[PDB]
Amino acid sequence: GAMAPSYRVKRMDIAKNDEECVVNAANPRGLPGDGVCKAVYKKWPESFKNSATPVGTAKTVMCGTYPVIHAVGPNFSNYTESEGDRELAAAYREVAKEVTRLGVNSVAIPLLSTGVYSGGKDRLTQSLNHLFTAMDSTDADVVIYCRDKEWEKKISEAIQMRT
Ligand SMILES: CCn1nc(C(=O)N(C)Cc2nccs2)ccc1=O
Ligand SMILES: [Cl-]
Ligand SMILES: [Cl-]
Ligand SMILES: [Cl-]
Image (cartoon, rainbow, N blue to C red; front, top):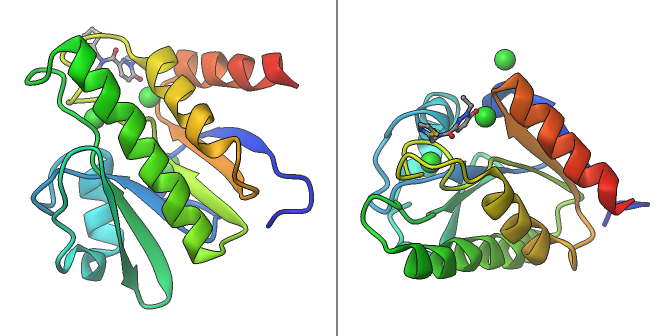
């Protein structure tokens, strides 16, 4: 584990992370997809061998010795708000189990279900709060990756509020 486990946020491509493993915002079928998923596919294509897994779960596949944790958040266009909230919290709990099992000291993570799976709604607070609930009991350094300047400021403020 990390000496003083922390949360940090960076506004950059998660495929260029400086952490010991990455969480992919995956689709259930292990397809290359779009957004974070396509960048992850271009950087670690070997990690997509048998990576298909149900919504609400996470499945790790090694690219060399680098772990790619494929986490499948719900698509809010298909799920109700209630059932979608439950699957989003579950996907993060499965990421925490995988990070612990791997024994890594750090992990790069995106905000699940905030892009094309958002159902057209701003889900920054909802997704980030489920991320904290799952990762707070782990001792890995967590680095959250985003692409928007206003989202970087809001995520940074949410982390600082707790310290
Ligand atoms: C543009 C800032 N930003 N917005 C979202 C967002 O809110 N999504 C995609 C859902 C929406 N679609 C229309 C309106 S709200 C996700 C990440 C991000 O950085
Ligand atoms: Cl970048
Ligand atoms: Cl998404
Ligand atoms: Cl973003």
